[PDB]
Figure 1 (tube, protein in one colour):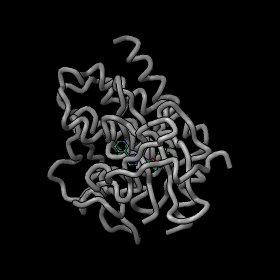
Figure 2 (cartoon, rainbow, N blue to C red):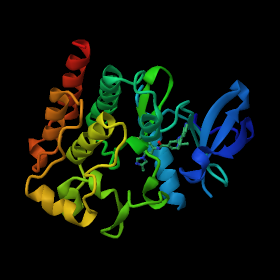
Figure 3 (cartoon, helix red, strand yellow):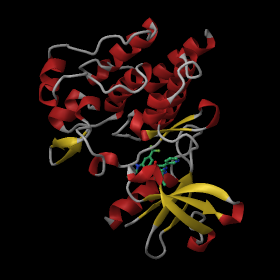
Length: 264
Ligand SMILES: Cc1cn(-c2cc(NC(=O)c3ccc(C)c(Nc4nccc(-c5cccnc5)n4)c3)cc(C(F)(F)F)c2)cn1
């Protein structure tokens, strides 16, 4: 296994994000004095599944697997470390003059490119959201999956069907039937686009979780955010079509963002 690496090659430092990611630590890969992120096992089959899945996925806009220590405990998964951290906090904390409308569009385009690649792989993300994306230099954005549903405080994730779901990002068939697919990822992408356009406001503001499904079923959808371009809102609306087969593919979504970005 070319992925196995020397646990000793890594100096472990502090928990990242002051603990909001669980057992993930800042590390230095001494061999290259490279700051990395290291997820450790504090659920063994689930952790090894994560590592195996990450070996088969590779894209400029997906978080980069660098290695694993799974030959003996405690197991590690090591990825690149993204300077600016998670997209949700980034948006909330940014200088909006720097991170302006053209930049927002560029972020969305990058996310759609990763999703297009995952769609080509028949890979189902299941938890697409700003909280699961990372920001690097020059507004580089990558999709990731921090396995947040058991750690996160608040009512982001709530009890549903025996697990915890981010109800407000979840497609109606995924809520009702536990049916997840590339098209439920498209639905969540539309919510992500609204997160981006509002610089990380919480979706369906003020609307209790217990009422969301019934509203959606009556064709209630979030309104266009202030200053979100019309074409971008049109794409949100398409992503939130009730019937999954009515939603666009990520190939179509990426092409549309590419065209809009070219024209800006
Ligand atoms: C069974 C299974 C697994 N996955 C899946 C796992 C991941 N993993 C991580 O992103 C992940 C794993 C380990 C580490 C160390 C990291 N890196 C990490 N985790 C938390 C925070 C940070 C961080 C914070 C601030 C600055 N830089 C990095 N990095 C990511 C990523 C994906 C995705 F999105 F790409 F498809 C999918 C899906 N199904």
